[PDB]
Image (cartoon, rainbow over all chains, first blue to last red; front, side, top):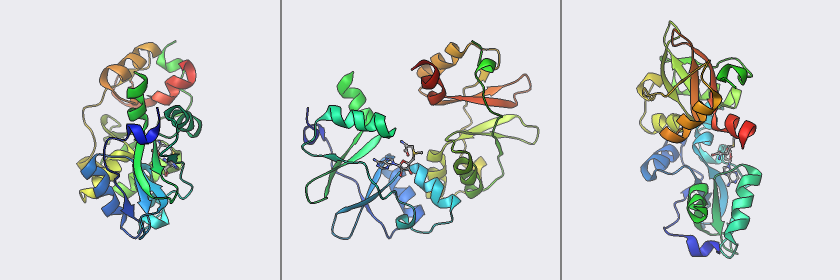
Length: 119
Length: 119
Ligand SMILES: C[S@@+](CC[C@H](N)C(=O)[O-])C[C@H]1O[C@@H](n2cnc3c(N)ncnc32)[C@H](O)[C@@H]1O
């Protein structure tokens, strides 16, 4: 079971220059809790969840780039699913962006996406 | 093991008239993702998570009352811990406020609390 295999839908990403409100609107619109942030060239630079929306409000930040998590735990398109599951238990995270060798975001894998593949 | 036997900290609550930003500050300060909302008597009236903070910002809500979830599953201090775990699975929830005879909040049990004891 590789990752590039189990991807079912397009990636949803955002740029870092956007407001906290715009980011929140994106989460709600797509009903997602993980939003990979890409630069103007489509390359991964960070990640946002609803926790970071709360954190931005608490720290009085205006843009996503001031609050996004910059050390992103990722999976490779050619990576095995079990390794991703272990990554997610180890770091206690529930979503990992899937990247290629050029750092483009090809999708995202969640712990619900995985929950299916084990049960 | 009753609920009262596993509570390890005081309750953390907020009033319904506080701003979205002020609620967000409470979540971040205490590193919690569930915030029971109470009235002037301390009676449970709702609950918020960081997801609700995001929802509120997206919708330009001003206070917590405008976004809080009012349909809140609870536990009593004298309820078996296992019965709380059963509720979490049954209603697909991750945080259960613990209430007393006046419906005041005396603590909260989370999914992580359960996994730490019984995972
Ligand atoms: C308190 S931790 C708990 C993790 C929880 N699953 C969440 O949604 O955030 C919250 C932080 O995890 C970070 N985070 C979530 N997924 C991540 C990932 N794949 N790589 C790096 N950081 C991540 C987010 O930036 C957020 O600020």
